Amino acid sequence: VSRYVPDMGDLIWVDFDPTKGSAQAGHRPAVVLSPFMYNNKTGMCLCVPCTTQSKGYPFEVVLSGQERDGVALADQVKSIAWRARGATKKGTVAPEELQLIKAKINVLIGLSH
Amino acid sequence: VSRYVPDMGDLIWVDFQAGHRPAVVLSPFMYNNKTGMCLCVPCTTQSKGYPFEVVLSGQERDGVALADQVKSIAWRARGATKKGTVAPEELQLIKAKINVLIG
């Protein structure tokens, strides 16, 4: 058995506990921003929190789901010890959604712009 | 009295015994002030040649910023204080390494 390794664009549950089921009351999922190679080597990844509680704040990025919608909180990027904390895959964000999250971070930090 | 609001490029002490660690602030004052949060990378004196280390040269003690370990931090509620400011070329470098981890 090999542990799941988070890949760029993946929507993951962090701190997964098999006792609150598919809902995970009290948790946020997260969009993975960093590449597989980095994630695999370090046991860490860069990711942004998600929530269904949209407020329409400037750094929100709408995640359009089949199931329902939510937002990535793009300003709140964090380095996460996925391997140590136990991550599971919930889904994958669309290419456009990932692009938009990165664009907003780029604005906030000022990287290429 | 107004609490110190971190600003882009500042080197701060933060709760990241309470115990603090130095961090470079990567988000602009306007954002930091409005949200009570800021983006920052942790610093260490212990260099190891590691790929995402950026050298920070002071006038006393030296170390590196660990550029890959970006963290959104509630400065407002954790008592960030200002210790200094990184040089522009140092901040630019930290941003280059992050840009690598993110398209």
Image (cartoon, coloured by chain):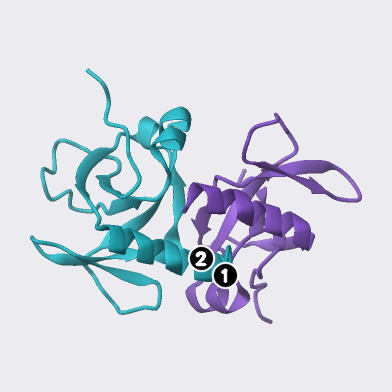
Chain colours: A cyan, B purple
Task: Identify the residue at image location x=36%, y=66%.
Answer: A100
Q: Is residue A12 left or right of residue B92?
A: left
Quadrant of the image occupied by residue A39? top left
Task: Identify the residue at image location x=43%, y=32%.
Answer: A43
Q: Tag on residue A49?
A: none
Crowding around mark 1 (Cα neighbors within 10 Å: few <14, some 14 to 19, many 20+) is few
Q: Tag on residue A106?
A: 2
Q: Earlier in the sequence, mark 2 or mark 1?
A: 2
User: Are the residues under marks 2 and 1 on the same chain?
Assistant: yes
Residue B76 in view, yes or no = no
Q: Position of residue B98 (x, y in %)?
A: 56, 51
Gap between marks 2 and 1, in whole Å? 6 Å
Numbered disc 2: secondary structure: helix
Task: Identify the residue at image location x=43%, y=45%.
Answer: A34
Q: Residue furthest bottom?
A: B1
How many numbered marks are there?
2
Q: Is residue B68 left or right of residue A38?
A: right
Q: Is residue A32 above or below residue B45?
A: below
Numbered disc 1: secondary structure: loop
Q: Position of residue B57 (x, y in %)?
A: 84, 48
**Camera-side residue of B34 and B96:** B96
Task: Identify the residue at image location x=30%, y=63%.
Answer: A96
Would you name the residue on which mark 1 appears?
A113
Q: Is residue A53 above or below residue A57?
A: above
Q: Position of residue A22 (x, y in %)?
A: 11, 46
- Asked if the residue at tag 1 contacts the one at tag 2, i.e. Cβ–Cβ closer than 8 Å, the answer is yes
Chain ID, mark 2: A
Q: Amino acid at mark 1?
A: His
